[PDB]
Image (cartoon, grey):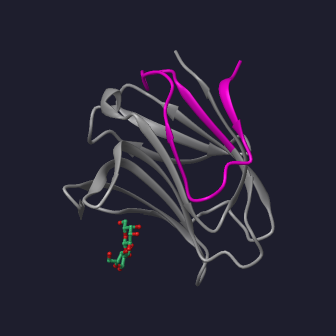
């Protein structure tokens, strides 16, 4: 029902993904936003190079300034594509969360706490994702996977 569970990873976290992100796969991330968070991001990456920065197939970036939002994008050759902004964000400072990223054939479907949050169409074949990055101001209790 969940495997390869990592507990209380230090952030910034970079970790190799166990198996392939095929349709049906779930990535489950449970955590808590620190009272002073400005933003954090979950990146599904092709590799872990820092300079040059590895490509990010799916950058999921809750931001907490202003009214707060979530920005989703794809980084290729150190350049960002078209941003998809979601203004209805379930993330709050000092509040805990469960993020479920479901890999569908055509898109990612993201729900927080069991409620649908956003969709993001595949720009890179998800089969090429091999690394999970979590950066910014966030406390992660656990990361887990349920493949296929
Ligand atoms: O697109 C993801 C990418 O955004 C960068 O910041 C953008 C910002 O999202 C945009 O709304 C503002 O108007 O311009 C900035 C120019 O890049 C981030 O710096 C980056 O971390 C990613 O989150």
Does residue 15 belong to the magenta stretch? yes
Which quadrant holds residue 64? bottom right
Range shown magenta? 1-29
The image shows residue 59, relative to residue 113, as above or below, that is below
Is residue 91 or residue 6 the one in the foreground? Answer: 6
Does residue 46 belong to the magenta stretch? no
Residue 40: percent from the left, percent from the top? 57, 64
Image quarter where ligand 1 lies: bottom left
Quadrant of the frame with the N terminus: top right
Residue 28: percent from the left, percent from the top? 64, 37
Residue ID at (47%, 21%): 19
Which quadrant holds residue 4? top right
- Residue most extreme to the bottom: 66
Residue ID at (33%, 26%): 127
Residue ID at (52%, 24%): 25
Residue ID at (59%, 82%): 65
Residue 95: percent from the left, percent from the top? 80, 63
The image shows residue 10, relative to residue 63, as above or below, that is above
- Residue most extreme to the top: 148
Residue 34: percent from the left, percent from the top? 75, 70
Is residue 60 or residue 9 the one in the foreground? Answer: 9
């Amino acid at each position: 029902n969940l495997q390869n569970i990592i507990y209380n990873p230090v952030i910034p976290f970079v970790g190799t993904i166990p198996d392939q992100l095929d349709p049906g796969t779930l990535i489950v991330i449970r955590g808590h936003v620190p009272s002073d968070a400005d933003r954090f991001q979950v990146d599904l990456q092709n590799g872990s190079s820092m300079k040059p920065r590895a490509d990010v197939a799916f950058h999921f970036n809750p931001r907490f300034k202003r009214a707060g939002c979530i920005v989703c994008n794809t980084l290729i050759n150190e350049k960002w594509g078209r941003e998809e902004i979601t203004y209805d964000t379930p993330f709050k400072r000092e509040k805990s969360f469960e993020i479920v990223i479901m890999v569908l054939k055509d898109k990612f479907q993201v729900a927080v706490n069991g409620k649908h949050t956003l969709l993001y169409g595949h720009r890179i074949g998800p089969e090429k994702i091999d690394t999970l990055g979590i950066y910014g101001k966030v406390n992660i209790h656990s990361i887990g996977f349920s493949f296929s």
